[PDB]
Every structure is written in C-alpha cells, then in structure tokens.
Amino acid sequence: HSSGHIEGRHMLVLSRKINEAIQIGADIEVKVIAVEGDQVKLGIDAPKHIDIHRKEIYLTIQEENNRAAALSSDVISALSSQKK
Image (cartoon, rainbow, N blue to C red; front, side):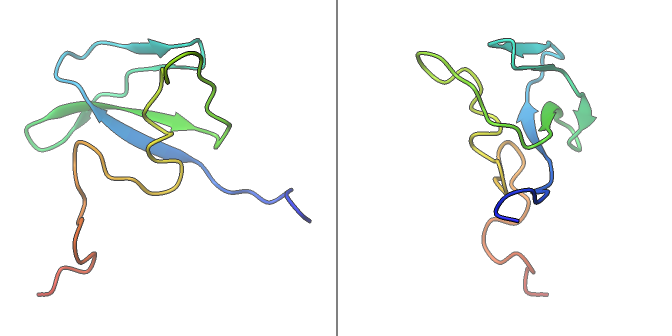
C-alpha cells in the first residue's frame, strides 16, 4: 500500500544487425536476438528496476520505454486498433 505494488516488467527491443552484446554501465547486459521479419534485433528486459546512468545516459533502452515505448519496430504508432 503506497508502493508494494508490482508494476510489472518491460522488454524494450533494440535493433542491432550485428548480433553483438550490449553491456552498459554494468546495469544492463544482454543480447536477445529476435526476428523482426527481416531485421535482427536485441531486447533488454528488466524487473522494472530503476535505470542507473552516469555522465550521459548509457542505457537509452528502458528509459525510453519503462512503460510503453515503440523503438526500432513501431507497433502501431497512430491508431492502435488500425481501422479495418
């Protein structure tokens, strides 16, 4: 009550056609290689922790998301139902 509530987790997709691994600031390290149709992308999933950075943000993944962002994919952008 007043916190103590699970605000879930988030996996924010980073598109990288290099299948390299992203190790930033010893907070986030992982390469989850997924099929984006014809694009290969990694994604960072976090237990909704706080995003630590130092001088200049080293993440820019979950701090762009942290709830519901659309990077290197664009789910629906305008009209999330898509009028069909």
